Image: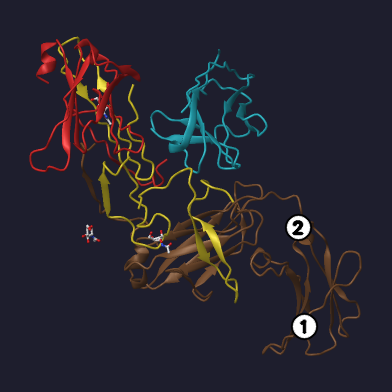
Chain colours: A red, B brown, C cyan, D yellow
Amino acid sequence: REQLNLRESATITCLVTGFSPADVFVQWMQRGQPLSPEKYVTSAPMPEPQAPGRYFAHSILTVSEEEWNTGETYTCVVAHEALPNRVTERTVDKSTGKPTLYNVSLVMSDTAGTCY
Amino acid sequence: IRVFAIPPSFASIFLTKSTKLTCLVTDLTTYDSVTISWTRQNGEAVKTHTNISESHPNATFSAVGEASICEDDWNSGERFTCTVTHTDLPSPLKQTISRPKGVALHRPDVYLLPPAREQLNLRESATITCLVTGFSPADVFVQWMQRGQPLSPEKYVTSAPMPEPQAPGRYFAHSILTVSEEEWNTGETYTCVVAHEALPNRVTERTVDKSTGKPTLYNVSLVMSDTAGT
Amino acid sequence: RILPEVKVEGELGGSVTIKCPLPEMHVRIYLCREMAGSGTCGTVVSTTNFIKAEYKGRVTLKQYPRKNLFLVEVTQLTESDSGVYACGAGMNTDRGKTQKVTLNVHS
Amino acid sequence: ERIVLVDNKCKCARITSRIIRSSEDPNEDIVERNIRIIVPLNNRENISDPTSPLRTRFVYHLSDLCTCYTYDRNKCYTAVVPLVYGGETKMVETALTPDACYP
Ligand SMILES: *[C@@H]1O[C@H](CO)[C@@H](O)[C@H](O)[C@H]1NC(C)=O
Ligand SMILES: *[C@@H]1O[C@H](CO)[C@@H](O)[C@H](O)[C@H]1NC(C)=O
Ligand SMILES: *[C@@H]1O[C@H](CO)[C@@H](O)[C@H](O)[C@H]1NC(C)=O
């Protein structure tokens, strides 16, 4: 939230943790259109502190603030050998994340016995 | 002298696979060589009966004549005739059984009413009423089950199908079941199961217990966890 | 959840027929006039022979399995027939409505 | 305007979300969580056998929300009813939900 208050650039980070061995891939897609390395970077692959079993890497994307009034959902796609389809696409936008207002509206009826 | 003409109930045609037809004699003298025969509308004879019954303690005889027919013949509306010939009456008496076609088939609606509040105050007995409305034609089969097993007809009484006020030809019927008062307060769920032709599955049921019929307690303990989640 | 509010005009002599969708599985198909004051729905036409007391003898049900339109017709209009007539299915009436529409008097 | 995040029909939860378009201010927006559980209040323990105690608990973990309380309107639930009519016992399939399914 602090970075978004500067209205300059929000950076989305994609963590690929617990993977072994190295050389795991990463790519960013905006609305299903491939994202080049001009606008994104990846941590060269790395190692873990408590367990030596798997190593970690990271990737961060750069954008503007007006872009986070529409989202475009900025999917982070990965490619590693220990994957069924070598793809584990994940995406997060403003709609998901931490919400600031819950209103549960549980109703109780004596005749809504088959939730239509 | 009296001779009956009992049409086969739907509870026979659908369950016993024995859609036969029987005519019973009564109010006659204790005699033999009774010629009770079933015939079709063309005058031809059909299969006969067996195992002639025994007389009644009222010093009146009782016998039954039976004929086995197929279901499609019944659903076509054929006029079968039972004829009784005896020395008592110089003229054989005929009785006609058929199916009057041209009547709509409506599906019964089953309503299970629990006993009234003031009835569960004398602490003597409770009456649960199974009301079937809208069904046409008559002759519907109804029975009761207590914890998944049926009961004898010595504890529940059904009523004859009577016409409906606002309906042209639809009917209604009542079946009351009386049980001990303490047999209804502890639980002991009762079910009313009915079987009329028009039902898409030909059999439906309803159920009541102490916690369902007009309850005085909505004991709710709803819990909701992991509101945020993923 | 369809809301095709149409402006079909009505009068004493005038007749207006509503159109409704049918599941065609011979369930309970009904047209129901919602009451604003009551907050519930009161069936004006049902699959059974029921007809509303105000609408006795002046309404007709017309079912075509061929064309997939379920339509009901009103013979005379007293000009008081202005409300949310919703169609539907299931045993239930209120919570089972499929499409709703409000008819109109004069024009 | 609201994305249908969950439309569960067996426990009847209808969780969803949206972004409320506030004024043209810094992005102090609000994310919505319109969870809408409906309580049957009259169903049984198993949904498909009317012989058990009725229903006390109503547990809703929204992580296993993407045994039931309610009845699916497009599904059919039936049972075997043990009728007799005399000596024979034709255990016949009944209907616990007349109108959601036809023979
Ligand atoms: C939940 O909140 C939103 C806006 O905060 C509101 O539009 C919606 O009606 C609320 N839900 C209920 C059930 O009132
Ligand atoms: C009401 O529900 C609670 C929760 O399980 C239960 O402990 C209690 O026995 C119930 N009360 C009655 C009268 O059954
Ligand atoms: C009661 O619940 C059990 C548990 O799933 C299930 O077999 C069924 O819904 C009910 N039992 C019977 C015998 O119908």
Q: Chain of mark 2?
A: B
Please state the horizontal and vertical placement of residue C87, each as a whole percent of the image: 52, 31
Q: Nearer the viewer, residue A47 or B1?
A: A47
Label 1 CB, ligand 3: below 8 Å?
no
Quarter of the picture containing the C terminus of chain C is: top right
The answer to which of D14 and A87 lies nearer the viewer is: A87
* The one of D55 and B114 positioned closer to us in this rendering: D55
Residue D5 seen anywhere in this rendered image of the structure? yes
The reply to whether discs 1 and 2 touch (Cβ–Cβ < 8 Å) is: no
Q: Amino acid at mark 1?
A: Thr
The residue at 8%/39% (across/down) is A49
Q: Is B111 rendered above or below residue B20?
A: above
**Residue B80 picture quarter:** bottom right
Q: Chain of mark 1?
A: B
Circle 2 SS class: loop
Label 1, on which residue? B50
The answer as to whether the residues below labels 1 and 2 share one chain is yes
Give percent across and percent down for residue D42: 36, 52
Q: Whole-Å distance between the Cαs marked 1 and 2?
A: 26 Å
